Image (cartoon, grey):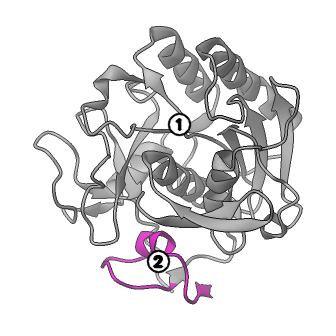
Amino acid sequence: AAQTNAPWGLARISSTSPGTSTYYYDESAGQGSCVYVIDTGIEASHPEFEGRAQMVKTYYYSSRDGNGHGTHCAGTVGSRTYGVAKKTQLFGVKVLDDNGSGQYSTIIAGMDFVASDKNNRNCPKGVVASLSLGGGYSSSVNSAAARLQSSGVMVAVAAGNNNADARNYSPASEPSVCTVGASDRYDRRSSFSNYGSVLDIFGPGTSILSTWIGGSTRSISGTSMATPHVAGLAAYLMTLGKTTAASACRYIADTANKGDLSNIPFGTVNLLAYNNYQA
């Protein structure tokens, strides 16, 4: 399949070179997989989701996305024009209020929710969770994300936008999940992206165009925008049968574009998510 004039990050993840604008992918497109988006909620009624998005859980007075950030991330996972996995199922878990913040105990309770709720869902090709959130180091937040991974979900988390070692953040610093940094369209590490030995992979993070609340679109930047590129890729790759939840992060790292990014500090991996699809 070929989507012309695609957003640059989509084209990048199906390209050995920067600077192109067509996204190539196997038409299976994540059919039969499920991605949980744990964030401010999802405007499921957005036409870009085609009835494939829905809210399954909130810890606040509404499951509505009154922020946009969770909607934007879900759009990068699986919307028709901006999504990596254009046929996946999207499940929203509103752990962040409409200002984008949430207590760690609420965040922990949402991760434990997904590790159980997946048993209430039809996802024969596998389960992914995309956590575009984070704060300072917490062993209880790390262990919550470890548990979710352990239950059989591929967990993708953002490295953080502090331009610093991600060892001091959570769940970025948990080793058993997939910690994602951000790059830009010239294959530079995004200026805000955290780095360090705990990072596993880079995805497109700067000026990422996706769905927004109110039926609209907009372009924003952040390692929360790289994370859903990798989450969506995992779901896409599990549907093709090329990997499982437990080994998706390692498979993505093994098959990535090596050595293509600049301003990657010594000791950080130089790997860019790549679907390796040959049209």
Q: In this view, does 161 lie above or below 145?
A: below
Q: Identify the residue shown where x is 34% and y is 71%.
A: 185
Q: Is the magenta stretch mostly helix, strand or loop?
A: loop
Sequence-wise first label, 2 or 1: 2
| Residue marked by disc 1 | 246
Report the front residue among 108 and 253. 108
Q: Is residue 109 above or below residue 175?
A: above
Badge 2 crowding class, 10 Å Cα cut-off, few under 14, some 14 to 19, many 20 or more, is many
Mark 2 or 1: the one toward you: 2
Report the front residue among 35 and 250. 35
Residue 34: x, y in percent? 73, 49
Residue 63 falls left or right of residue 147: right
Tell me where the magenta segment starts and ends, as one range: 1-22
Determine if the magenta segment contains residue 115.
no
Is label 2 in a helix, a strand or a loop?
helix
Q: Identify the residue shown where x is 78% and y is 34%.
A: 118
Q: Identify the residue shown where x is 56% and y is 50%.
A: 231
Residue 137: x, y in percent? 40, 16
Q: Which residue lies furthest to the left in this view?
A: 266
Q: Do the residues labelled 2 and 1 touch (CB within 8 Å)?
A: no
Residue 251 falls left or right of residue 93: left
Query: Can the viewer see residue 83 in this picture?
Result: no
Quadrant (top left, top right, bottom left, bottom right) of the N terminus: bottom right
Determine if the magenta segment contains residue 4.
yes
| Residue marked by disc 2 | 11
Q: How many labels, in total?
A: 2
- Disc 2 to disc 1, C-alpha distance: 27 Å
Report the front residue among 259 and 263. 263
Residue 159: x, y in percent? 39, 38
Picture quadrant of residue 155: top right
Residue 131: x, y in percent? 57, 37
Q: Is residue 80 above or below residue 259?
A: below
